[PDB]
Amino acid sequence: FPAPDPSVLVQNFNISDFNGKWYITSGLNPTFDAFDCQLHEFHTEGDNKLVGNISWRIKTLDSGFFTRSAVQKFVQDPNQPGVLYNHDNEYLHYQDDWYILSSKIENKPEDYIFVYYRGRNDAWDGYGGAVVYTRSSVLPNSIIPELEKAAKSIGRDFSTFIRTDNTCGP
Amino acid sequence: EFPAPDPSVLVQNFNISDFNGKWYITSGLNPTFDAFDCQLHEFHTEGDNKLVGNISWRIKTLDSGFFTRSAVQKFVQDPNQPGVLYNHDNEYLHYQDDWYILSSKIENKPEDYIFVYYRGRNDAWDGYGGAVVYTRSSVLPNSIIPELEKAAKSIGRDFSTFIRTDNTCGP
Ligand SMILES: [Gd]
Ligand SMILES: [Gd]
Ligand SMILES: [Gd]
């Protein structure tokens, strides 16, 4: 997961377009929760920040667990609108960086944002992947050509991505 | 143990099509470590008898990897007891999940709720169960709490012990 060339990122991006409900309907590097509900609702904070809810779990010596909600907040790069940083993490001690490869926002059913992500913490510096957020719970057929072009721009191939439609859903 | 509840304590009328659409689980008697992940479920009705939604299946393999799949889970309503729904139904998955509707208010208002007590079994264990509140809202409404306390009481439980999980899909 090397950082992308700045030239392959969207050159303009308004973090306000991340507001509200988005489904993750495709991903490069899924986990075993790939088919659980993939709805995320985000909120903008001010000018340059995006906020959403995350969850924290510890597994203890009795086979029990403790869990908590937390926030994850991203700040946009002031020179590269397609780069967002979440370093931000206090007790949690990790960094997650987002790179917007491709996006179409027409306030239409087919709107999407394609994010490549990379991360690190004390245990490992290898974290990363790529996900497609769509307004629709079903990835729209019409956006696949642009997704294929975006994936190819970072040396990937979109046909390798897992497809996860209607994950909450009807 | 989660025994079968007294039939008299269940809702005496229930229309399964009232389960259609989007519901959030905003409270539960016994959570798993995924309690704070998004608790949105979208249900639909099949025929006039059956409630359907999407579930997920995982296996963890010897190499530390995994395989996963979407599946569906289908409930049928008991014809004599509107508040009893059965998911036996399950093919190669080999499990049973029974739902007992303790309390519900459906008025097509933001505070609508359905309070489900559940019990289950598979080859590994017969001890599965718990109780969850489905709400139309992503936040459990303060106004339904006295009915929930009463419903919890009817099966020998206390609503105050339940986990509260508001805004689980985002702020
Ligand atoms: Gd990699
Ligand atoms: Gd750095
Ligand atoms: Gd029990």
Image: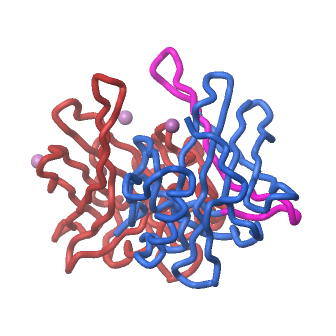
Chain colours: A red, B blue
Horizontal arrangement in the rendering, residue A61 relative to residue A122 (left or right): right
Q: Nearer the viewer, residue A125 or B154?
A: B154
Total numbered badges shown on the rendered structure: 0
Query: In this orientation, does residue B31 appear?
Result: yes
Q: Quadrant of the C terminus of chain A?
A: bottom right
User: Where does residue A117 sit, x and y in percent of width and height?
Assistant: 33, 50
Q: Quadrant of residue A77?
A: bottom left
Please state if B154 lies on the left or on the right of B88 as rendered: left
In depth, the one of A140 and A36 nearer the eye is: A36
Does residue B147 sit above or below B117 in this rendering? below
Observer-nearest residue: A70 or A128? A70
Q: Residue B35: image x %, image y %?
A: 42, 49
The secondary structure that dominates the magenta segment is strand
Q: Is residue B66 magenta?
A: yes
Q: Quadrant of residue A57?
A: top left
* The N terminus of chain A lies in quadrant: top left
| Residue B82 falls within the magenta-colored stretch | no
Compared to A30, does A113 lie above or below? below
- What x and y, as percent, mark residue A46? 20, 80
The structure residue drawn at horizontal position 63% and vertical position 42%, both measured from the top left corner, is: B119
Q: Residue furthest top?
A: B62
Residue at image x 71%, y 59%? B8
Residue B119 vs residue A55, the one in the foreground: B119
| Residue A148 in view of the camera | no
Q: Residue B78 placed where, x, y %?
A: 83, 55
The residue at 41%/68% (across/down) is A41
Residue at horizontal 47%, vertical 67%? A22
Identify the magenta region: B43-67
